Image (cartoon, helix red, strand yellow):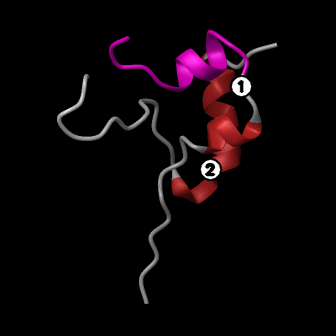
Amino acid sequence: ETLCGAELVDALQFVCGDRGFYFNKPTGYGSSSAPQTGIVDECCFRSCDLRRLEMYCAPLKPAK
């Protein structure tokens, strides 16, 4: 059905891997912030798909 609490973190840990993850979707400057909203709203309170969930993975960088 949905992903919450520990299940949500396990999912984020598995999908994101070494990259790590975050919970609040970015908003961008001099904007509004429905206050601070993110993955709980998208994947726990409601149903989300893999592509949505993967948007909460942090970058990788790299550096050459």
Residue 34: in magenta span: yes
* Secondary structure mostly seen in the magenta stretch: loop
Disc 1 is placed on an element classified as loop
What amino acid is found at the position of numbered circle 1 in the picture?
Cys
Q: What residue is shown with label 1?
A: 48
In the rendered image, residue 59, in percent from the top left (x then y), is placed at 48, 59
In the rendered image, residue 5, in percent from the top left (x then y), is placed at 60, 17
**Front-most of residues 15 and 54:** 54
Q: CA distance from mark 2 to mark 1?
A: 16 Å
Query: As drawn, is 1 to the left or to the right of 15?
Result: right
In the rendered image, residue 53, in percent from the top left (x then y), is placed at 65, 36
Query: Which image quadrant is residue 30 in?
Result: top left
Quadrant housing the N terminus: top right
- Which mark, residue 16? 2
Task: Report the label total.
Answer: 2
Outermost residue to the front: 31
Disc 2 is placed on an element classified as helix
Q: Is residue 37 above or below residue 17?
A: above
